[PDB]
Amino acid sequence: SYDDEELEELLRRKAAQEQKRIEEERKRKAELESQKESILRVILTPEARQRLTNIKLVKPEFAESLENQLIALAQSGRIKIPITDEELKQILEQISQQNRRDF
Ligand code: NA
Image (cartoon, rainbow, N blue to C red; front, top):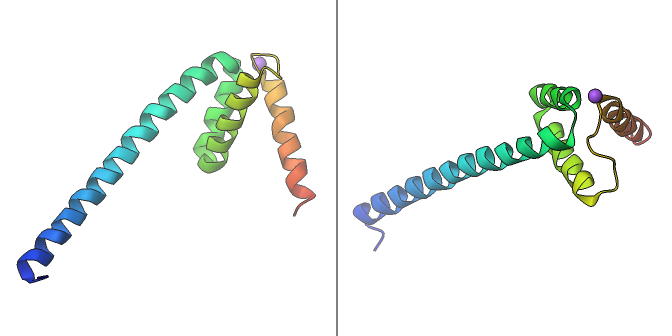
């Protein structure tokens, strides 16, 4: 009927669904981020992992993309493991130079 009582409890159903949706998003990101850090501990040297942790503080979206890509590169076996801070700096300089030529 969409009388007042139905609108009230449909909108309550929406608040409950948004809360659940957002609680589930917060939980999934925390657990997946935990497992990505467990991979980064083994695939990066301590100094390289420290640099990526620092990048995540200042450029979180960039850092999340870079984590996913380093994890894929390591799984692929194409690159020697662990990735050193020197090697991570070369990857970052390559990204920087590739985006200057596309600026
Ligand atoms: Na290193």
